[PDB]
């Protein structure tokens, strides 16, 4: 942990300290104790105070007294020393002055020219920097070359023959955690390729023809069309999960980038089916250089799946076997960033050499070719490691205390998980934007999901947006206008309430065109919340309608809560707009922002449907099938729960805004009720594209994150009636595909603006006498002569969707929709589901009849 540092050096000439004569002490050898200083200077207290530039950047110290540093002081020399200020003694946090004096916008990393190669490293506090060249990926150091410094930037220019060498920086710098000037070996923060485990940086030209698959430069011409961000659907997928169990893929490609180049596999046939039905984007879990998995496959440990398959469904033996090797197996979600700009070595066929670059590109190209754009899960909010030691620490090894956020005592913030980054610092902001550009241009990535976006400054998000949009096919080989951004706008810990500045929270990102996950519709549909009691029911898990026995109040309470969830869901169905007006369950008209969650938050908060990512499931927390298996009454058949799964995914698939699906939603995927399977190996994360199993009942999930819920898991996992058969899995997939086809059969499901939604979208089952467990959504198009709106749909003039979660058939009379030519959607008329085909419309009364646990879409044809 970093020492006590309650003072801030914010500008070349200002130090901030919240004390009630102050002196500055410096030691280039780090030889101070409490003595041992080489230099000292008195700081004259500032009358005016801290400049606006400082307080805007570091709001949390706006009350700190200001102390002026004499202009005769050699600040550039001092920031390379061990420093303390005395009143009481404490260290100083330097990011402010480092930015003020050494903000750098020139090239970083390697730059290639015809006859030379240059290296640039930002290390403003270092006393010395050299580059070490190695004999390949595993050989010894062959040569050391000193770099020269200019305003905090170290560089050297060498011959073009430096190309394809391996290197590391040797950085001599004071490390507060060790209270010593240490000589550290570090990779290039601007690395474009690495040896196994990033032990060395590969000095490769990312633009070289030999690193490009055939037709790579023309990929823009092959990319799937995207008319509007409102046409986006997203499928969230882990790279290893995808092919780890796919026997149709060669053993040598399974689990990595190459598996996507196998178009004839069950996995890729699965994705093509979804893609052909309308799915537009595949969101891949972290695929950059992260820690937690050895790049060297021959170091991997595996369990015997044939053996674990013989253990009882609710036994603790499976998780014991996995946990025993989980630190050295091939598996991890990958949320442990080391270097952002390089593909993960473990996902390549060979961690050394060009394969990781070539195969990543082959992956994007393959996905593009089957109609899918690629989204990267980016994790700019924190680092796997900090400190001077370890192969997993890079940034904080080179410029200690700068890239990571720290508290007012100088301790590193860990709220994100560990080693939070400080995007509010100039060079952190730059690195993030440079990285995004790297993936967009060098890998033609189509979009980005931002992990913990609330931990990132909004100005970083907005500049990245403008930088990405500026990319053109003629200048950069990619159309930046089609690149889509979204993230987790969660507001918590040290960044909450704009404490470190305007951050990327849900509320702050309203009106930015950048999406954020809608946790309101998620919890309203499933019930409860990721941290509450697992048995808390929701709109689609039996609240009021089908009590699961867990006491949740009298029926009056549960019915009221159900109606409340219904309101929240409907606001979400209309793009979760802050200004959309809904007739609430009380009969009162309310804007989306005036309808509140149980904890006082505005339900609707966006300025556009494209700012809303509607979801009911994701990689974190329980899968859709598992959450439903836990919250619904145990008496239900798996056949009924299968229909419940489909209702949930259909609520997303037919909502205004951007639907988000967790890989497996469509096939009843289970993790044996694992709520946090980040380290649960292939066993608990199994994706089965033979459709013979869904991975339910493969033992209690790892105790680390699940033990407290084991008692409720065991009875369900052991019950044969909870497990679906192939027939169920295939049925869910067929119905999922049909609902996707319906979304893309009419533009009406995908309105692009708030004005269009306010004008065309109406909910028909509202008020105090609303029918519980039913949502009716109508969407109008231009009809008759002199229409008050444009005509968007050539085939239909009106669409009505009925979500019926009641266990029984319902008849909804909508007089406003009488005397119209509604028919069940042609997709459902020809459905393999015999239930939905019993849906009906009655023109005389405008009565819609919809079977239990069914979503029926009715259309009014134009012809
Ligand atoms: O940062 C990673 C985190 O991101 C997401 O979480 C966000 C979530 O999606 C948002 O919706 C929102 O959460 C708000 C929530 O919906 C509100 O209801 C309320 O929550 C309060 C609870 O209702 C209340 O019960 C109490 O909860 C306590 C629990 O009862 C108690 O069990 C314990 O919880 C522990 C969890 O059981 C355990 O799983 C573990 O949680 C980790 C998760 O496993 C992991 O996935 C990740 O969390 C994600 C989350 O999945 C995303 O959806 O990290 C978690 C780290 O802990 O540990 C828990 C330890 O607490 O404790 C909790 C309370 O401490 O309190 C809460 C808070 O009032 O308000 C929420 C507002 O925060 O935002 C979150 C992120 O803020
Ligand atoms: Ca497609
Ligand atoms: Ca692991």
Image: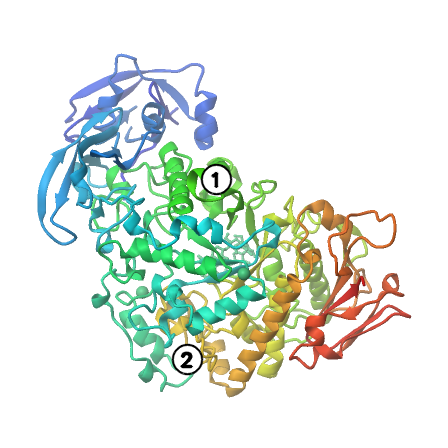
Residue identified by numbered label 2: 698
Q: How is the image coloured?
A: rainbow
Can residue 227 be seen in the rendering of this structure?
yes
- Label 2: few (<14), some or many (≥20) within 10 Å? many
Instruction: Please name which of the two marks, 1 or 2, marks the residue nearer to the observer.
Output: 1
Where, quadrant-wise, is the N terminus in this rendering?
Answer: top left
Q: Nearer the viewer, residue 525 or 825?
A: 825
Residue for point 88% across, 51% down: 785
Give the Cα distance between marks 1 and 2: 49 Å
Q: Secondary structure at mark 1?
A: loop
Can residue 533 be seen in the rendering of this structure?
no
Q: Quadrant of residue 411?
A: top left
- Label 1: few (<14), some or many (≥20) within 10 Å? some
Residue identified by numbered label 1: 472
Relative side of 735 to 375, left or right: right
Relative side of 231 to 771, left or right: left
What numbered label is drawn on residue 264? none
Q: Please provide percent x and percent y for residue 17.
A: 37, 26
Is residue 95 shown above or below 572?
above
Q: Please provide percent x and percent y for residue 41.
A: 24, 17
Q: Nearer the viewer, residue 516 or 314?
A: 516
Q: Nearer the viewer, residue 424 or 827?
A: 827
Q: Please provide percent x and percent y for residue 389.
A: 20, 47
Which numbered disc flags the more N-terminal residue, 1 or 2?
1
Where, quadrant-wise, is the C terminus in this rendering?
Answer: bottom right
Q: Quadrant of residue 634?
A: bottom right
Residue for point 32% across, 84% down: 306
| Number of numbered callouts drawn | 2
Relative side of 96 to 452, left or right: left
| Ligand 2 within 8 Å, label 1 CB | no
């Amino acid at each position: 942990f970093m020492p006590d540092a309650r003072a801030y050096w914010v500008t070349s000439d200002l130090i901030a300290w919240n004390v009630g004569s102050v002196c500055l002490y410096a030691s280039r050898a780090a030889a101070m104790s409490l003595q041992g200083y080489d230099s000292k200077v008195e700081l004259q207290p500032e009358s005016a105070g801290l400049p606006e530039t400082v307080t805007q950047k570091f709001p949390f110290i706006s009350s700190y007294r200001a102390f002026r540093v004499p202009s005769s002081v050699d600040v550039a020399s001092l920031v390379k020393c061990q420093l303390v200020v005395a009143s009481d003694v404490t260290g100083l946090q330097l990011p402010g002055v480092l930015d003020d004096m050494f903000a750098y916008t020139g090239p970083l990393g390697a730059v290639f020219s015809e006859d030379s190669v240059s290296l640039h490293l930002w290390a403003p506090t270092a006393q010395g920097v050299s580059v070490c060249f190695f004999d390949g990926p595993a050989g010894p150091a062959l040569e050391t070359v000193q770099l020269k410094e200019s305003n905090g930037v170290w560089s050297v220019t060498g011959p073009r023959e430096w190309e394809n060498r391996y290197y590391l920086y040797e950085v001599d710098v004071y490390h507060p955690t060790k209270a010593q000037v240490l000589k550290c070996l570090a990779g290039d923060p601007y690395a474009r390729s690495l040896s196994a485990n990033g032990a060395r940086t590969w000095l490769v030209d990312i633009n070289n023809e030999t690193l490009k698959p055939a037709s790579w430069d023309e990929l823009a011409d092959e990319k799937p069309k995207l008319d509007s961000f409102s046409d986006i659907t997203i499928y969230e997928l882990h790279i290893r999960d995808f092919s780890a169990h796919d026997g149709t893929v060669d053993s040598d490609s399974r689990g990595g980038f190459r598996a996507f180049a196998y178009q004839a596999s069950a996995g890729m046939e699965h994705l093509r089916k979804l893609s052909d039905a309308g799915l537009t984007h595949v969101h891949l879990l972290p695929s950059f250089h992260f820690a937690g998995v050895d790049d060297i496959k021959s170091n991997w440990k595996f369990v015997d799946e044939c053996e674990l398959a013989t253990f009882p469904p609710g036994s603790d033996m499976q998780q014991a076997a996995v946990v025993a090797i989980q630190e050295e197996d091939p598996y991890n979600w990958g949320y442990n960033p080391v270097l952002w700009g390089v593909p993960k070595g473990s996902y390549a066929s060979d961690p050394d050499g060009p394969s990781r670059i070539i195969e990543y590109r082959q992956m994007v190209q393959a996905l593009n070719r089957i109609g899918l754009r690629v989204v990267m899960d980016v994790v700019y909010n924190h680092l796997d490691s900090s400190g001077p030691c370890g192969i997993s620490s890079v940034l904080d090894k080179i410029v200690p205390g700068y890239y990571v956020r720290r508290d007012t005592n100088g301790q590193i913030e860990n709220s994100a998980a560990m080693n939070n980054t400080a995007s509010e610092h100039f060079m952190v902001d730059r690195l993030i934007v440079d990285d995004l550009l790297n993936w967009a241009v060098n890998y033609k990535v189509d979009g980005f999901r931002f992990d913990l976006m609330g931990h990132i400054m909004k100005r970083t998000m907005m500049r990245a947006k403008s930088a990405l949009q500026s990319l053109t096919t003629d200048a950069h080989g990619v159309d930046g206008s089609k690149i889509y951004l979204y993230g987790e706008g969660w507001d918590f810990a040290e960044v909450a309430r704009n404490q470190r500045g305007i951050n990327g929270s849900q509320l702050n990102m309203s009106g930015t065109g950048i999406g954020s996950f809608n946790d309101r519709i998620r919890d309203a549909i499933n019930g409860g919340n990721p941290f509450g009691n697992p048995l808390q029911q929701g709109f689609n898990t039996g609240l009021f309608l089908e009590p699961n026995g867990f006491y949740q109040g009298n029926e009056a309470d549960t019915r009221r809560s159900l109606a409340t969830y219904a309101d929240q869901i409907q606001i979400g169905l209309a793009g979760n707009l802050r200004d959309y007006v809904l007739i609430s369950h009380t009969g009162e008209a309310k804007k989306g922002s005036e309808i509140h969650t149980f904890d006082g938050l505005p339900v609707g908060y966006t300025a556009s449907p494209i700012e809303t990512i509607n979801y009911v499931s994701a990689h974190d927390n329980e899968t859709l099938f598992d959450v439903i298996s836990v919250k619904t009454p145990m008496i239900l058949s798996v056949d009924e729960r299968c229909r419940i799964n489909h209702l949930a995914s259909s609520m997303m698939a037919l909502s205004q805004g951007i639907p988000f699906f967790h890989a497996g939603d469509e096939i009843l995927r289970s993790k044996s009720i694992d709520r946090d399977s980040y380290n649960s190996g292939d066993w608990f994360n199994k994706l089965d594209f033979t459709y013979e199993t869904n991975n339910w009942g493969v033992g209690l999930p790892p105790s680390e994150k699940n033990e407290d819920n084991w008692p409720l898991m065991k009875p369900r996992l052991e019950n044969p009636s909870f497990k679906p058969a192939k027939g169920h899995i295939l049925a869910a997939l067929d119905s999922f595909v049909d609902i996707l086809k319906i979304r893309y059969s009419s533009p009406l499901f995908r309105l692009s603006t708030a004005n269009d939604i306010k004008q065309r979208v109406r909910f028909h089952n509202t008020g105090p006498s609303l029918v519980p467990g039913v949502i009716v959504m109508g969407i109008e198009d231009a009809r008759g002569e002199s229409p008050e709106m444009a005509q968007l749909d050539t085939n239909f003039s009106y669409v009505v969707t009925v979500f019926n979660v009641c266990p029984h058939e319902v008849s909804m009379d909508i007089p406003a929709l009488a005397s119209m030519g509604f028919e069940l959607h042609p997709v459902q008329v020809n459905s393999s589901d015999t239930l939905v085909r019993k849906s009906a419309y009655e023109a005389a009364t405008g009565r819609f009849t919809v079977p239990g646990r069914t979503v029926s879409v009715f259309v009014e044809p134009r012809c």
